[PDB]
Every structure is written in C-alpha cells, then in structure tokens.
Amino acid sequence: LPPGPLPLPGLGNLLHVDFQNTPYCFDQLRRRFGDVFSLQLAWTPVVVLNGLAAVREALVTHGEDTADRPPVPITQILGFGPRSQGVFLARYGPAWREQRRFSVSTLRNLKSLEQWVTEEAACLCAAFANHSGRPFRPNGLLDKAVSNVIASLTCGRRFEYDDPRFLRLLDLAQEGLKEESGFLREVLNAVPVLLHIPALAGKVLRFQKAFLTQLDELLTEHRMTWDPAQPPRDLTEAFLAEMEKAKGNPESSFNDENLRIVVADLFSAGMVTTSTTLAWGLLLMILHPDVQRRVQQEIDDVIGQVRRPEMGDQAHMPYTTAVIHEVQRFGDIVPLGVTHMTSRDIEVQGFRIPKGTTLITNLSSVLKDEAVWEKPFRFHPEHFLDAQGHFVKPEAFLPFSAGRRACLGEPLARMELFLFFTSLLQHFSFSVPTGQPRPSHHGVFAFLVSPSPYELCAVPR
Ligand code: HEM
Ligand SMILES: CSc1ccc2c(c1)N(CC[C@H]1CCCCN1C)c1ccccc1S2
Ligand code: NA
Image 1 (cartoon, helix red, strand yellow):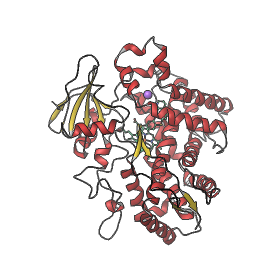
Image 2: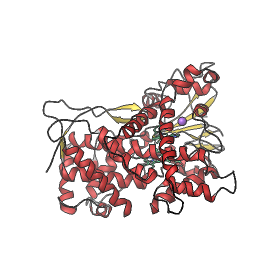
Image 3: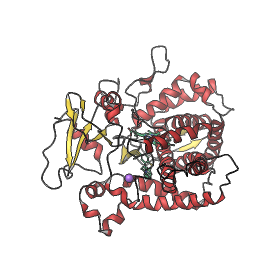
C-alpha cells in the first residue's frame, strides 16, 4: 500500500536512488510520497520508515514481527554460514539470541571497566597535549583511544598509538565501513553478476575481507596463548570457554567460524561509532564555545580540575549529559540505522507492509522529527532540559534505535562518551585555529555520517 516511484523493468529503481548519498534521496522522496514510502530494488521489496511514529510502530509496537534481518547475498565472500552469522546481521532466532545474550552478559562482569576508560582517557589527553599549539585532526586519535577500550574487553590487551598492526586495523575498519554503502554493493546483491565474476566480487567488501584476516591473525595469536585454568579476562577467552563447554552439539552457535565474526561485530562497532561521535563532539564545541564553557564550569563545580571523572558524576551533571545527548542527536551518526525485515504482515501508519519486506528505519527523521524538537536542525542542548534545568531524555531520542535489535552497546557507549568527553574538556579547551575559517556543520556520508574534515588546537586549563 505505501506510495512509491514506479520501478523501471530489470534493475528496478536502483538507478533512481543515489547510494553514495542515500539519506539525501530518501529525504527527497519523503517530500513527494510522504512519511512512509516504498521502493523496489530489483526483486527485493523495500519500505523506508520516516519519522518517530512510523518507526516506533514497526520496531516496538510490531516489534515481534520486525526483529529479523533481511538476507544479504554478497555476504558469501566473507564466507558466512547459518552456523556462523555473528550478531549484527544474524537472523531472528536462537543462534542470534545466544550470541546476543552472551555479548551483553560477558561485558558486565568484565566500576572495574569505569576505571579502565579513564586510564585510556589519560593516554589520550597526553597525546592531545603533545600538540599544544599546532592545529591537528583529532579524528585519528579518538579512533585509537576508543579502539583500545573495545580491544581490552575483546582482545584482552590494548595497543600502542604507534603500533603498525593497530593502525592497519583502524584503517581497514573505516575503509571496510564505507564499503557497506554504495552503488556496487546494492546492484551486486540483486543480480547474479557477482557470482563467478571475480573482477567485481573481489573489489566489493574487499577491505572487510582484509580486516577479518587481520583479526584472525590476532585471534589465532590470542587463541594460541589461552590457558583454560584461568577465568576469562576478555570476550575472546570467554568465547573459547563456551566453545569448550558446548562441544556437545554441533548445533551450538559457539564455533571457530563464529568466533571471528562475533568478535569482529563487537570490535568494529565499538571502534568507529563512539569515536566518530567524539569527533562530532569536539567539533560542536569549537563552533559553539558558549556551550563548551558552560559544560567546562559544570565539570569544575562537580568533578573539579584535578580528579578524573566518574560515571557517578553524570547524575549530578544535567548540562554535560544534555550536551552529549544533543551531540548524538545532532551528530546523527547512523541516519538509516540497520536494515530490518518483516517476519509477517504488519501495519504502519495506515498502509500494510507484507512479509519479507526490507525495512529501513530512518533514525535521522526521528532524531530530527519536526513534530518533536523545538529546534530540529540546530545544535540546541536545551532539547534535554526542563524549566529548572533538569535533564530529560525524550522518546524520539533513538540514536541506538529500538526494539529487540536495539544497540547492545549503548551501556558501553554511554560510559565511553561521558568519560572521554568530560576528561577532554576538563583538562583542555578547544578552539578553531586562529587563521583557519569556519569548519562546516555538515557531515560526509559513508554509511555513517562523520564530521567533515577539520582542525583544532588544544590548550590546557
Ligand atoms: C555512539 C555509539 C553507537 C551507536 C549510535 C550505535 C547505533 C546502533 C544502531 C542504529 C544499531 C541498529 C539497531 C537496529 O538494528 O535496529 C545498532 C546495533 C548494534 N550495535 Fe551499536 N551503536 C553504538 C555503539 C555500539 C557499541 C559500542 C557496540 C559494541 C561494543 C555496538 C554493537 C552493536 C551490535 C552488536 C548491534 C546489533 C545487535 C543486533 O542486531 O541484535 N554498538 N547500534
Ligand atoms: C550501526 S551499523 C554498523 C556500525 C559500525 C560498524 C558496522 C556496522 N560494521 C558491520 C559489522 C560487520 C563486521 C564484520 C563482520 C560482519 N559484520 C556485520 C562494520 C563493517 C566493516 C568495518 C567496520 C564496521 S563497524
Ligand atoms: Na556485510
């Protein structure tokens, strides 16, 4: 029932959409066909969901029937199997629930973690300071800091900012991540041209393949040293202990094939999502020093200029919390979220969506819904503050989406964000370089929006 552009025969309408700037075209279609609209990519049926109401209805109200994930043809090059699907793209079932339940459970046992982020935050602060006067791109440093946190939890160790193996991981990660979006990936899935045609099959997802084999290196290295008599200190070990405990049946999702994919899912996700947000954070603090100052004093009032920040401070810091949430909302890191699929027929905003329809939850249309925020497209921290200035998180705040598939990294993310953000502003003040012009608000698109290239200088307080 949703209204869609007519699909030209053969390729469908995958021409009509620009996959190197997707969020734009989905907005340009939302203005003719309205809030809910549907497009055909070749055989595949799709129904883009825009605005809070339409999203919440599918993911929460009809959540039990939209938790599944649509199949990806091009995954074959990675070598995915029903046996090993990881978490991120695994189909709604026991294999997914096992790894999902294992993931969040294992992170919790691994206060202790709280201290570890601040430790890493130091090494970051230092790296920052070591360029006191000169302008520099903080994107790369943040990437390293955040990556060491998720590395600890999963690989048991942290890496030096100079380590070649480490920097190669980071690079492949960001490049692999771009691969997720584009023209070639979408059209490959649709038609069997990918198969038995090495020329394209090789080029697409290439970096991710290079990324995984650099992970397998780290894993086999890590596996070789795993001593069973020692309780797990990292997820890899914890997983290995499960592979031992569950050697009984080959049906279990705990296997060598899954280990690399699961660890990849968590390791990669922690690496870029938080780090990009922190890049947006610093940016919005140099283009809005007025907001930067207010936070900076609040820090001094509660935390102080001398002791490292602790999660227990967030409670007593309404502005810093509202800014961060605003940074995420405005940042709009993951515009179209992650593709969903209907397990059965459902109804959204009147229209009726048939089973097997790929769903695209446009979180941007929610994070910036006109009927919710007072100043949607402007950086307005007061979107999370009431009359007496107490923090309040609105429903429409869904940077982590919602439903059974909602981000299982939110707790970690929340922890990482607040601790890194405050630790930075506490010991530093960030301004645009004197000579340099105003850096753009707008963000480049590579599946996830990132702050357009910019520089800043960091000076102690
Ligand atoms: C600012 C930080 C982050 C943002 C904005 C974010 C956002 C998202 C979004 C939009 C989804 C899709 C939800 C859906 O399918 O409806 C998702 C899923 C997921 N995220 Fe994140 N995430 C962040 C951090 C993390 C971290 C730190 C981890 C792991 C350490 C992580 C791991 C995952 C996993 C495994 C899934 C898939 C879960 C499933 O499919 O059941 N994320 N996240
Ligand atoms: C919120 S959607 C999101 C957010 C951050 C990342 C990614 C997706 N992925 C996908 C995970 C991928 C990892 C390999 C095994 C199969 N799985 C699905 C990614 C892909 C490639 C490089 C970096 C990353 S980090
Ligand atoms: Na993929």
